[PDB]
Amino acid sequence: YRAIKGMETKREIGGYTYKVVFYENVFQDSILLGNFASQEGNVLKYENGQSCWNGPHRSAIVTVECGVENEIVSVLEAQKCEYLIKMKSPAACS
């Protein structure tokens, strides 16, 4: 279970372009979602993004699962500053 480091993965969701750059940072349109803090296997935690209320800054958990290509699958608001994003990648398979 790996994810391709250095690559930009971007996908439009809800009208906004989600962009995840592996081992760097994530953006939603132009908003800084989160910076990569820690990741295990194929599940990546990004936090300390752009300031939001009721949270310190944005954050998201990306779960990169088995897929054919590195694509953003879904982004669901977990709390408000934190979102659960599902992704797929061939390297996240086995």
Image (spheres, rainbow, N blue to C red):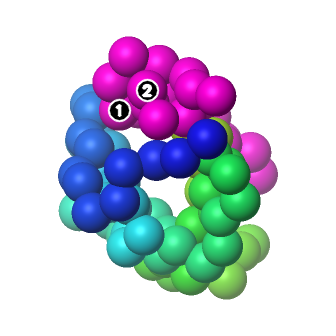
Residue type pointed to by label 2: Pro
Secondary element under disc 1, as helix, strand or loop, is: loop
Tag of residue 20: none
Tell me the distance, in whole angstroms, between the alpha carbons under discs 1 and 2. Answer: 7 Å
Residue type pointed to by label 1: Asn
Secondary element under disc 2, as helix, strand or loop, is: helix
Direction from residue 90 to residue 65 in the image, left or right: right
Residue drawn at the location 68% of the way across and 51% of the way down: 41
Residue placed farthest to the front in the image? 94
For the question of whether residue 61 can be seen, the reply is no
Mark with earlier residue (1, 2): 1
Residue drawn at the location 27% of the way across and 63% of the way down: 6
Give coordinates of residue 72: x percent, y percent: 41, 32
For the question of whether residue 66 can be seen, the reply is yes
Magenta-colored span: 65-94
Please tell me whether residue 2 is drawn above or below residue 75 in the rendered image: below
- For the C terminus, the image quarter is top right
Please tell me whether residue 85 is drawn above or below residue 61 in the rendered image: above
Direction from residue 42 to residue 49 in the image, left or right: left
Q: Are marks 1 and 2 in contact (CB under 8 Å)?
A: yes
Mark count: 2
Disc 2: which residue = 90
Disc 1: which residue = 70
Residue drawn at the location 67% of the way across and 83% of the way down: 56
Give coordinates of residue 19: x percent, y percent: 30, 50
Direction from residue 82 to residue 30 in the image, left or right: left
76 and 37: which is toward the camera: 37
